[PDB]
Image (cartoon, helix red, strand yellow):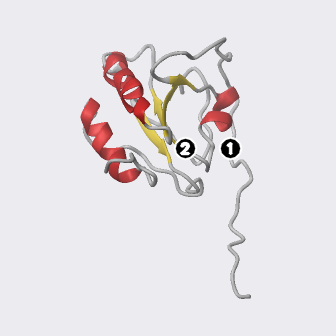
Amino acid sequence: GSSGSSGFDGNLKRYLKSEPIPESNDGPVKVVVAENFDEIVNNENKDVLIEFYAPWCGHCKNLEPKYKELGEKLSKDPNIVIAKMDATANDVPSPYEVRGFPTIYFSPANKKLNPKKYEGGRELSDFISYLQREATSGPSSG
């Protein structure tokens, strides 16, 4: 017949620094490090949201609790998985680019070639409504 999407995928990423893998991430937001970045972040099976922050930054720290919630909040989403990664602590892959922090990003499904960058209000809810429409899969109710 006449069909077939060759596409393209080859773990397009690169990093020089990486943080140690956590013994267990039994919390609201999954800890994603350059070491296990392409493991949790990269995944065309389920949607994932990566949030880059800095321990030295004050504006980003005050958000820690503002972002955490979202993690346990979206827990009702077997498709969406919230996670965080310390850029400064671990180099960021590509095309993922982080010049100014905080830096929030989103890893869509089968959209690796062209990711997404959260550009709006850093409000717990603002994040939910953002995915409710962005997340290809989205929640059952909506």
Who is closer to the viewer here, 51 or 135?
A: 135
Does residue 91 appear left or right of residue 128 in this picture? Answer: right
Does residue 72 appear left or right of residue 42 in this picture? Answer: left
Q: Quadrant of the N terminus?
A: bottom right
| Amino acid type for the residue under numbered disc 1 | Lys
Q: Is any part of residue 96 visible from this angle?
A: yes
Location of residue 6 in the rendering, given as x and y in whole percent from the top left corner: 72, 71
Who is closer to the viewer here, 109 or 12?
A: 109
Location of residue 113 in the rendering, given as x and y in whole percent from the top left corner: 59, 57
Location of residue 85 in the rendering, given as x and y in whole percent from the top left corner: 53, 26
Element under disc 2: loop
Which residue is disc 2 drawn over? Answer: 96
Element under disc 1: loop
Q: Residue furthest front?
A: 141
10 Å crowding of disc 1: few (<14), some (14-19), many (20+): some
Who is closer to the viewer here, 118 or 25?
A: 25
10 Å crowding of disc 2: few (<14), some (14-19), many (20+): some
Who is closer to the viewer here, 53 or 127?
A: 127
Q: Is residue 26 above or below residue 12?
A: above
Q: Determine the residue positioned at 51% across, 51% down.
A: 115
Location of residue 86 in the rendering, given as x and y in whole percent from the top left corner: 53, 23
Q: Residue furthest bottom?
A: 1
Is the residue under label 2 in contact with that under label 1 (CB below 8 Å)?
A: yes
| Amino acid type for the residue under numbered disc 2 | Tyr
Which residue is disc 1 drawn over? Answer: 13
